[PDB]
Image (cartoon, rainbow, N blue to C red):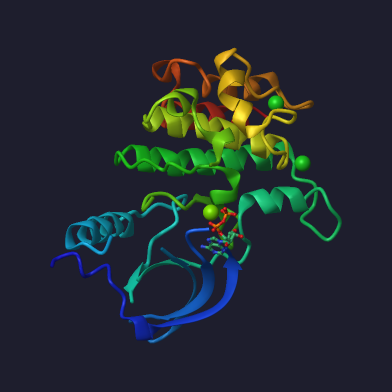
Length: 260
Ligand SMILES: Nc1ncnc2c1ncn2[C@@H]1O[C@H](COP(=O)(O)OP(=O)(O)O)[C@@H](O)[C@H]1O
Ligand SMILES: [Cl-]
Ligand SMILES: [Cl-]
Ligand SMILES: [Mg+2]
C-alpha cells in the first residue's frame, strides 16, 4: 500500500526508439514531471503474485531513495507489466566511450589522470551502495554511465552470464556478497586501464572457473603503473575476506591520482 509513491502514472510517460535488447528491452522515453517540464528517460521493461510484486516495489522505493553523484537515480516505476524509469544519459556508457577514445571522431586520447578519476567515481558510488548494504551484482564498465559533466555513475544494479566479471567463490557456489562486487570492480578497473578490452583474452567463458582456480588472474596492462595494478589485483584475492572494502579502494585511488 505505502510503496505506491514509487509508481509513476503511465500517461506521464512517452516511449520512443529502442536503445537495446533477452528478458528485457530498453527504450528512450519522455517523462512529464511535476515541474510541468519533460525529462528524457531510459525505460527498461521486465509469477503475478501480490507477494512478489510488493517485493519489487519495496526494492524500487529503496533505490529511489539513493542520492549520490556517482549513483544513477531511479525516477520511479510504471506498471502496465513493470517498467523502470531512469534519467537518460546522452553520453552513454563508459565502455563504449573507452572504445571510441581509440578512434578518430571519438573523444581524444584519455590520459591516465582521467582514467583514474573514472575509477574514483565508480569506487565512490560503490562505497555509497555498500554503506547501505545494497549489492550491485552486475558491475562492469558497460554499466557505468557518463553524466553530462562527464562524472561516472554506477547503474543497472538491483531488481535482478557475464562470467568474466563473476568472483571465483560466486562461480563455485550460490554466493554473492559485497566482496564479489569488489571482484567485479577490479575487472571494471582493468577494462578502464585497457580502454575497453574484453577480460581474459584467449580464455573462453566456460574455462573461467578452472583458470581462476589455478590462480591465474587478469594480466597487468602494458603501460599501467605498478601501483594501479596492485589495487586491481587486491580485488581478486582468492579469499573474499582478504579483498579490501570499497572505502579502502576509493582512498587508494584518490591518493594515487593525487600523486601524479
Ligand atoms: N540511463 C540510460 N541512459 C542512456 N542509455 C542507457 C541507459 N541505460 C542503458 N542505456 C543503454 O541502452 C543499451 C541497453 O542497455 P542494457 O540493456 O543495460 O545493455 P548492456 O548489457 O550493454 O549494459 C545500452 O547501449 C546502454 O548503454
Ligand atoms: Cl579491445
Ligand atoms: Cl588477461
Ligand atoms: Mg546495462
